[PDB]
Amino acid sequence: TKLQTIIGMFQITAWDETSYFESDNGAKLTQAVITQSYQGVLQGHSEIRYLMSYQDNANATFVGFEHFTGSLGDKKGSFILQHKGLFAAGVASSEFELVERSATGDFVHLVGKGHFVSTENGQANYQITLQDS
Amino acid sequence: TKLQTIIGMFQITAWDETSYFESDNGAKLTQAVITQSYQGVLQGHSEIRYLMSYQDNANATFVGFEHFTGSLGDKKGSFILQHKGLFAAGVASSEFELVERSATGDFVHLVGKGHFVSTENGQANYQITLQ
Image (cartoon, rainbow over all chains, first blue to last red; front, side, top):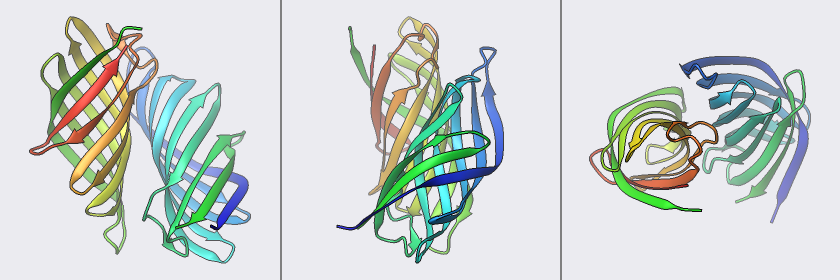
């Protein structure tokens, strides 16, 4: 069994969000299109789309797909991460998994999972573990 | 704790899907805007949005939110279901949960989760347990 775990940071460079439902409450449903950069061991760029359900301006859940293109050491390719997220008390966090059979290039035949927690200024710390087969 | 489980069917009445990424493979990323109708003890209509990741035309995962407006007997209101779904072997299935603090009207304070499995003709069987 071979596993590779990477701990790092990402930077959000753009965040484009459009509501499709808004109630007097302050609750809303939105779609967000986000771009993020990764530097370090994991190096690349992601385009992400999330659907978000806000119960109020400070509390939401979000789900979606992150399309990563880049490299991890000698491996080059792309993959899709499926995200299950929460936004509470000014902090966004997510649990994600690599979508089976979504990977290309040197990332084929790998499973993976991880999480992230936001910090400040569009940054977040993440951990991801990729495993063979 | 008093629990009740409702088992029924829903009918897709509209489904519009738009790709935002397509690969030479047949893989694609899409958004789907959907409407469904519910008849029975759970009676009403839902407006749904899903994001979908297709590995090929026969296999996909989907996630999103269903906004239901209607009644559950004498109780009237709305709520949001958060879905985690799979399409495989010609069957769509989802596990969902009622989003906390999303419910309105007589549905405030409802807690719940369930699943659905598609049948044919735009229909699916669902089960939902609420508190």
